Length: 41
Length: 51
Image 1 (cartoon, one colour):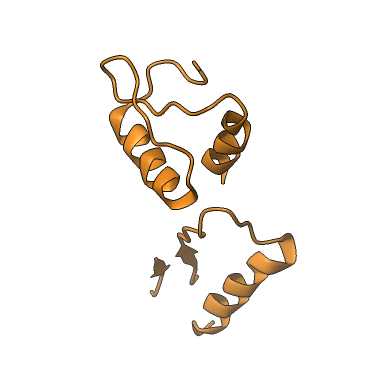
Image 2 (image 1 turned 60 degrees about the horizontal axis):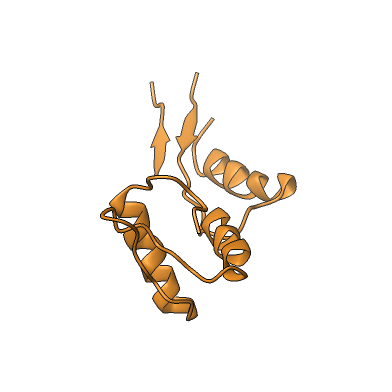
């Protein structure tokens, strides 16, 4: 569930991972830098 | 075995689904319908609950 703040811009993603797994610290940066660079500014 | 006390019926049903998935019998409790399993499987069942 991705949400944007378009008027300083910001984004909020609510990810429900598959039961029985957990992304690592360098793995959350995946969705973080994906939704950040999918949004201008 | 009283692994958990007075679990809700939704939790019992979900564990029943996962138990149909695995193999361990998906039993009920005293008028509450809370899953019950053999003595050894409670460990791995609670591990599945954690997952």
